[PDB]
Amino acid sequence: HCYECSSDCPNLQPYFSRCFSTPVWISQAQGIRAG
Amino acid sequence: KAKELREKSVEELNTELLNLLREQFNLRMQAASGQLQQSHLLKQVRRDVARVKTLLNEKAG
Amino acid sequence: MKRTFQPSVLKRNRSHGFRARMATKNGRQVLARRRAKGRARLTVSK
Amino acid sequence: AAKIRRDDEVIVLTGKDKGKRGKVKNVLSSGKVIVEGINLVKKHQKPVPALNQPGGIVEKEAAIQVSNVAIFNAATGKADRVGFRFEDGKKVRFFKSNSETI
Amino acid sequence: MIREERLLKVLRAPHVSEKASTAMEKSNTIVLKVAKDATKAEIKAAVQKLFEVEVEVVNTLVVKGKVKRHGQRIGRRSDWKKAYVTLKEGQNL
Amino acid sequence: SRVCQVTGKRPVTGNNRSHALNATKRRFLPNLHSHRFWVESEKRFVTLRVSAKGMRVIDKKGIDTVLAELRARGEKY
RNA sequence: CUACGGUGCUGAAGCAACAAAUGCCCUGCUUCCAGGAAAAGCCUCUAAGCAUCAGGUAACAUCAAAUCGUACCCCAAACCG
RNA sequence: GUGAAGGUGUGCUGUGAGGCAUGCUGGAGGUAUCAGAAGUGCGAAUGCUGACAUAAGUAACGAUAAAGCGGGUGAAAAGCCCGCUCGCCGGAAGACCAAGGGUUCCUGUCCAACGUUAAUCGGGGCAGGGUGAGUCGACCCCUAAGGCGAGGCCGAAAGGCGUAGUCGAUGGGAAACAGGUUAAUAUUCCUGUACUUGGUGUUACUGCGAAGGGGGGACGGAGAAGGCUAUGUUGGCCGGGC
RNA sequence: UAAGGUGAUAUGAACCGUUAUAACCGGCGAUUUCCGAAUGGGGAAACCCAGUGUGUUUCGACACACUAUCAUUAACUGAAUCCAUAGGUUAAUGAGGCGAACCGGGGGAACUGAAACAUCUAAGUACCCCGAGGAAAAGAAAUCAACCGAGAUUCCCCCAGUAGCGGCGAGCGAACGGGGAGCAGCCCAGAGCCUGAAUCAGUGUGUGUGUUAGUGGAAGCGUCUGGAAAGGCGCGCGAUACAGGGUGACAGCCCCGUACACAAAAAUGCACAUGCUGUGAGCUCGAUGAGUAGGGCGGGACACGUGGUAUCCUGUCUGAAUAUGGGGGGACCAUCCUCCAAGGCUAAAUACUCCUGACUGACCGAUAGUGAACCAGUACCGUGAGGGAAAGGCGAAAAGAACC
């Protein structure tokens, strides 16, 4: 009865491997003072 | 039928091309109307109009 | 807010359309590269 | 040039009916051959409201492979192979081992 | 004045709808599926010659093909043209 | 384009070589001028973007002889 | 009417005064300087041309007006995110 | 096939990588030996792909405009339908075009998945149905910016530029309104009343005729009124109430 | 060529045929919408709008044909301007577009190496453009050699990592000569005698041979296990065929084939035989390719970076000799050897494979092998150029599970 649909991933990440991993744009961590 | 037509004149050939499409229109109306349980005359008449238009465009030249 | 893609078919077909690609040498090379790849849709057109 | 045709009383050489004799009903396309009363299966035919609404366990005959049958000679009493000769300008099926026309 | 074998190819099928039958009973309008390149003059010439009746006005529209999903793919049905042929006062077919 | 109509001198390319031998690309353009030549056969003036080497081919060979080598070649004048 | 949903037959009055736009008169009027598209449709003039021809003009009569779009969403669950 | 590889146990023995035997699965292939050739051995490379954990049945369930009841249907109703209240928006959270989308429209059906819950519901699935134009829009005629551009001028080549010309609306050119209608279309269908342009059949007096001429088209900002109207408000009238 | 068919997912439904046109396969032919070089003008490909003929017309119209630009040529008529050109028109021809690599030409990097870097390298590579062919280009000595000689180009093996070149660094890297593959030379700058005189082409019958459908093929049975035998055990037969595949497990003998022997209406490739047409022989003589060679300047190519440096090309400026003359032989000169530039054509050996046919593999076996074993350049993503997946296996046969 047309079942066992898949897990359609987002159309943003073309490497489905990291599709659910990181957004891959900007990494903002701002508190770093080393001197 | 493919052989009986090559003893016809061109005006004889053309007036049965008129009767074939009037038959083809008769059958195409019948198939949509819920009638025409014999749903094989369509393929037969469509290849009868092609059989005579072939024999038309060959004695034309 | 206002995103980068604001669609208009007229601005689409004048930029990337088949006649826009067939106007120049470097667009007929685009269409040559998209027949050589085997692309279903050649341009943005239909 | 088929060696096994429409109405031939054939004998089955292989596969649960090895030895049984029947008549071919129709040669299909893919080398499968329906033989009369030979390769019986048990079809759990589901009743649809129209179109043979008797929906029993219908026993039909399944297709057998065309290489698993041979034509029964019946003038020797055994299975027999087929060859092709030209008699009277016609391609003629004939039995092996006695060379006589079918 | 249209050639006769052209008129024999425009009228595809009479269209049944329960809107089409409302038009046949209340406004004397037969609704026909026609060929895709049918003009309103070619339909008017074909309903009069082949259905042997009289025609006032043909109104046409083009029905868009629905996108259907048979199995797992994405198909699209054909666009077809639909006439609204208004016969004058005497109705045969 | 900077082509002599008589000798066919294209611009050719080569190098600039400095005193430290740094090669960089340049072009040796031909010494082209458009000049009107009097022909007594045609009783007219005819202008030709010709090199200064081509002006020497013309008076050495003739202006009828040069133009006959252009109509039989495919140049337009 | 009749499932009273609804469809169906009926259907009286249908005036006046006042206040009114950012809308129309107005592409006006006044005024300013920063001095505010183009071409056709349209009216008009004729040239070559043209002869009670061809056109034009009016009224009257006929026919023709093709072909596509037309559902639905539009401050949005149908558009861009 | 009286059971191969593989998988899974067990036992035995080699100094080790390992080897062998076999019980069960498996249901068709496997290879003593001696040589031969290597995509020849993985735990790591913030390795690559798939699968599955963990946090954790935790956080969250997307505007604090708000819901409560009674019937209905149903296997099941907080959410669907109907009803009565209640709350919210009203220069919008309403109505309508262009763009963009492309059937999401309407009906009957289903409720797996989709819907941040349930769902009988849905912009979900499925199958039908639905878009009707001389007048609305496009097309079309006209051009603006700008594009392309015969010849042309340039340029190693590709090509750049540009004249004639030809395209290009966001502008200019032609004409329909009101009621009624469908489950879904309406200035399109139907009633009523119009109107526009072009092709085609007679009169008198007849000069008509352009890739031309001249009008006209044809145009700013602001400001100020007056004349109205849409619309509203009250009175009157009319129907009904007590 | 046939007893079966009406392509696939795909069942039907309605049928067609049965030995002579059911389908299938091939040759040839017809048809071949619309867009696209797109060519009637336009355009936002798959649409919009015509012009002029020609018909036919119920008078509403309807068909079919033509209508691009350019190049070359011809015809007509044609400015300033008298002649005359330019232009203008109308014909005929031909061209354009796409295509994977190879090929020739025009342009032309940088990263990198040098342990930095600029000369040099990478590399005349990547790329861009132009043009062509089945190959292309080169090609008939202004060549080499060394006092003997060789005898057009191309390719391969040596010579030889030599000689050299070189911030004499990194690196670059020959020839001569030798072994081979394949080996043809010819024209014009020119007039005569002779006078189709072989040639080399195209076209057409004719033959031989492939290609495009095909045809015939040779022989095994019992028996045990098993769901089923192709396996085991027993006993035969074919073999110019024991290549392979399929069949209920592993088949020479069941099937399809294979070895072999054969076949062509028709259309084509190749040779040959040629008939008929185009070029055009052989002999006598003359002729012997000038803004060239060379030079000055600046670059480039040669292994060769201007160095003592030949030779080639040429942007610029000059400028011979004309066979009793000229080039080269690695600066230059004299000898004396060798060749005759400034015109052109030219097969094979060579390079390549989009594509077709077989055939093979110490190649892969679904995370591999193509990106793609599967409706894959797809779904998806991006405005776009572009990127780009994942996803094979029931069984021998659906017998794919009636009924409760």
Image (cartoon, coloured by chain):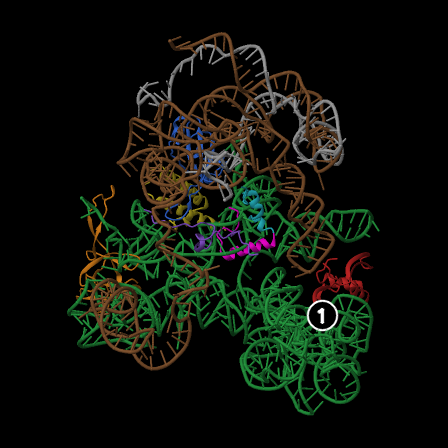
Chain colours: A purple, B yellow, C cyan, D orange, E blue, F red, H brown, I green
Q: Is residue D88 visible?
A: no
Q: Whole-percent x and y of residue B42?
A: 37, 44
Q: In the figure, is residue C40 to the left or right of D97?
A: right
The quadrant holding residue H39 is: bottom left
**Residue at horizontal 32%, vertical 46%?**
A1
Q: Whole-percent x and y of residue A33?
A: 55, 54
Closer to us: I88 or D34: D34
Q: Amino acid at mark 1?
A: Leu
Q: Chain of mark 1?
A: F
Name the residue beneath numbered marker 1. F21
Residue segment shown in magenta: C24-46
Q: Whole-percent x and y of residue E48?
A: 44, 32
In magenta stretch: residue A22: no
The total number of labels drawn is 1
Q: Whole-percent x and y of residue E66?
A: 42, 41
Closer to us: H135 or I88: H135
Q: In the figure, is residue I82 to the left or right of C18?
A: right
**Residue at horizontal 56%, vertical 43%?**
C10
Q: Is residue F3 visible?
A: yes
Q: In the structure shown, which secondary structural element does the residue marked by tag 1 occupy?
A: loop
Q: Is residue H19 above or below residue E63?
A: below
Q: Is residue D14 above or below residue A2?
A: below
Q: Is residue D36 above or below residue E63?
A: below
In magenta stretch: residue C35: yes
